[PDB]
Amino acid sequence: KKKDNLLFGSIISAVDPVAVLAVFEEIHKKK
C-alpha cells in the first residue's frame, strides 16, 4: 500500500480501444 502518485491515470486511463487500435492493429498483424 504505497505510491499514492497516479495522476497520470487521469490521462492514460482515458485511452480507449480506438486509441489502442492504431497500435493493436500492428500487433495482431505481426503475431
Image: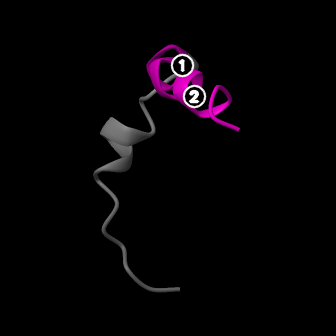
Classify 9 as above or below 18. below
The image's mark for residue 24 is 2
**Residue toward you, 19 or 23:** 23
Amino acid type at image mark 2: Phe
Q: Position of residue 1 (x, y in %)?
A: 53, 86
Residues at marks 2 and 1, CA–CA distance in whole angstroms: 5 Å
Determine the residue positioned at 44% across, 85% down.
2
Determine the residue positioned at 44% across, 28% down.
15
User: Element under label 2?
Assistant: helix
Q: Position of residue 8 (x, y in %)?
A: 29, 50
The image's mark for residue 31 is none
Horizontally, residue 5 falls left or right of residue 21, namely: left
Determine the image quadrant of residue 25.
top right
Q: Main secondary structure of the magenta part?
A: helix
Q: Is residue 28 magenta?
A: yes
Q: Which residue is mark 1?
A: 21
**Residue toward you, 12 or 10:** 12
Determine the residue positioned at 37% across, 80% down.
3
Q: Classify 10 Å Cα crowding around label 1: few (below 14), some (14-19), many (20 and above).
A: few
Amino acid type at image mark 1: Leu
Q: Classify 10 Å Cα crowding around label 2: few (below 14), some (14-19), many (20 and above).
A: few
CB under 8 Å between discs 2 and 1: yes
Task: Point out the image quarter for the C terminus.
Answer: top right
Horizontally, residue 6 falls left or right of residue 29, namely: left
Determine the image quadrant of residue 28.
top right
> Which residue is situated farthest in the bottom direction here?
1
Classify 13 as above or below 21. below
Q: Position of residue 9 (x, y in %)?
A: 38, 47
Horizontally, residue 12 falls left or right of residue 31, namely: left
Write down the region rendered in magenta. Answer: 18-31
> Which residue is situated farthest in the front direction here?
30
